[PDB]
Structures are given as C-alpha cells and as structure tokens.
Length: 125
Length: 125
Image (cartoon, rainbow over all chains, first blue to last red; front, top):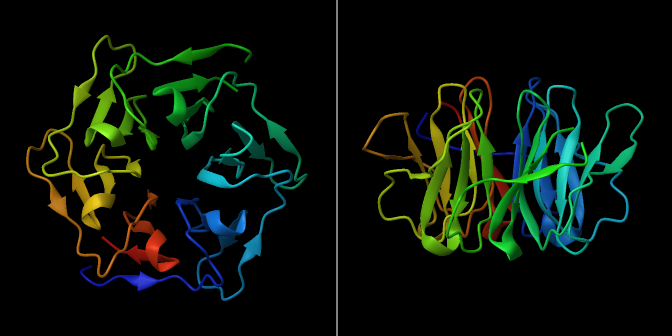
C-alpha cells in the first residue's frame, strides 16, 4: 500500500514505541502521559494496561504469550506484565542507565538498549 | 536468569532501538553515530547495514524474512532493507514528525509511532 491509515488511539502525547501481537492488537508507549495503551484491530476503545510505578515508558515489545515488556526511563528498569494475572515483574537487569528499546526473541530472551551506558544487554527469562 | 550478557557491539553512542530476528541476529539503532549495526548469534564482529543518509535513527524492527525497518527520525521517514540488499526503500508514509517506534506484523503491515504528531500510523504491504 502507498497510503497510510491513522489508528484510532486518543489523547496521546509524544508516543515513542509500538508493538503488535498475532491477533493484530497494537501496543503503544504513550510517553507524555506515562502509560501504555492497547487497541485491538477494528476497535474504537483503547485500553490502558495496568503497569504500576512507571516513570515514563521508552519502549515496548510483546511475546507469543501476550506478555508485554516495557522500558522505564526514570526507574532505569525493564518490566513485564503477564497476561491474565496482570502480575508485573521487574526483570533482574543491573546497572541500567536509561533503558530505551526492548526486544524479545523466540526463546524468551530479553534484549535492551542501555542508552546511557552505550551498550546492549540481554537476559534470558 | 540472573546472568545478563553485554553484547559485543562496539563504539555505540546513545543507542535507542533493538530488534532480534528468528535466527537470533540482533539489530541496534546506534543513534549517535547515524547507523544501524547488527550482530549474528555467536558472532565476533558487528556489521553496519548499508542504509544511506540516516540521521538520528531511533526505532528498529525486523520481520520473519530478515527485512530490517528503521525509523530514520532525523529525516521524518521510515526506511527498509531486505536481507542482502544494498538499496534501501523509503516507505510511502505521509507527513511524519519526529517519528520513533516501528513495528511489523505477520502480514507485513508496518506500524509507526509518529511522535511529533501524537499519533500512530499503519501501512499495509
């Protein structure tokens, strides 16, 4: 296609990260509003995810289990949110300084760009 | 795991996006050096992808075919490179303003957080 569409998210401010799962559900780090929002394919209502203690999200990824991974700018950490239980787990990375991008491979290994430390770190689940 | 591994990228500056493909190849937007670097799984040396004219790139994604998608933030555009190709393609997005995140679904649809415009746009293959 040569013509984009705009997704019907609302009230975004400086969004900075996006991920999409197998059902076509789109996840966005709404940076300026310190929240993570998702929109199912073909929906008008967006859903704010129950991340807690977030201090400005920088990036997002989603795995095959529907687990959502988010880099937290102000807390220098990476968190994941389990589907269903909505349990939030802080990944035991250490020495991060402004994690930004996050990615997850098929084996569940988590990769993070450590922006303040000029390095890339990975951590198996 | 309580073991994190620093990947053998070198000379990074303010890196800010990471992606990993099905073969375990890792791609990073080395934002401060206007380049995208990659490292094969178990590889000794990073390789710079032959993108042209990148300026403060930020987001990166990779699809199941190994095609690499980069938000070329400083140029308000999204570019992609097929594996082995030496000629990037500028995707026909419209009116982007300081874009950041990019994602790609199984159908090849490309999603971009158009940060400066407080919106998320989508472009089918």
